[PDB]
Image (cartoon, rainbow, N blue to C red; front, side, top):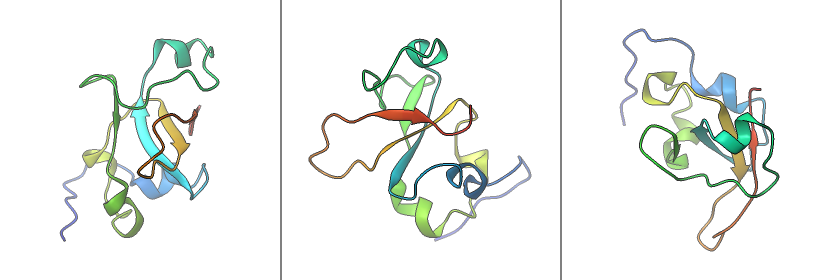
Amino acid sequence: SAIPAPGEGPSVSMAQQKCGAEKVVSCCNSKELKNSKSGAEIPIDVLSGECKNIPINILTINQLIPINNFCSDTVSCCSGEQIGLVNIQCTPILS
């Protein structure tokens, strides 16, 4: 497993720290979130360029991966999406 790092900027380790380790990392600029009108009514996975859930598999050990493999957006950390968590709440990591 290789970590791509040309020279974009910081790594996910910086962002993830500001949320619970049991929470899943996703970058999404939602209109509801941007207006602070979402307690649980926020979709993690939406459209290519707005919101997407990023694979948590690498995120644990490959946290050394810089944001170049991530979306610079209002970062959201949602309840750890394990198989069965069809609906959960998302909250901004860095706001």
